[PDB]
Amino acid sequence: SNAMYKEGACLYRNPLRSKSDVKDWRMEGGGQISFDDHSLHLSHVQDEAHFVFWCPETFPDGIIVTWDFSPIEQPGLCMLFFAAAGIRGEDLFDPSLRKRTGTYPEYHSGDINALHLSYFRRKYAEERAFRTCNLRKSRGFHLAAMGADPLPSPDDADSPYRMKLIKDKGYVHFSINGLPILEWMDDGSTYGPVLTKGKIGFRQMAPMKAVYRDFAVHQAVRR
Image 1 (cartoon, rainbow, N blue to C red):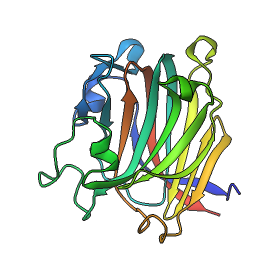
Image 2: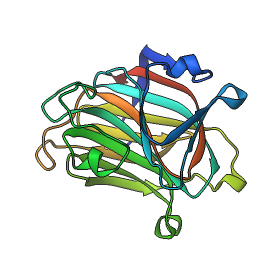
Image 3: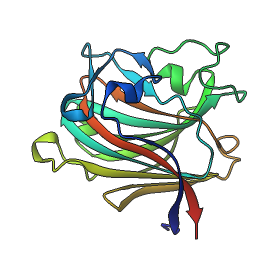
């Protein structure tokens, strides 16, 4: 449990402080972008305008992903997509893939594969009644792991929170403020081959309002 990993060379770092920082990012769905206080504010144009906002860079396998997160207003839900690519290995933005509009089934039951970890799952009463973070693997919407979510409701927040995700072949580990939340080891024969490289994206279920800062990707060094 909690195998030792160190961050290696920095592969990518985005402060997310101004519009120029998300210049080539791809917004799928009705997300609203703002940079008040020199930080990325993500909201929605309508109450059910769910979306996925993608970083355009293809990241390799064996990485540690970090970012600052601040839950500002609920109801809502957040989710990080990673190791995302076409089912045949196509670039997530290759024109040959079906168009996506932020509608969930397009991501878990479409023509792409990806790991997706939901946190601050507070969109529905059932979710707010038992707070957890869930890790799924698609295509297939397969539940891989879950753990309790220490994130409070906005009223009691002491933002931002330090999010850290490790992805190294079959291994996935997630922590918040250094506290391990969940971990998983894909054997590669239960829910298909192990996912490797791919895009990273930020999803929100409306009417979520959140702030993101200092998104970085480092090489994962296994000790």
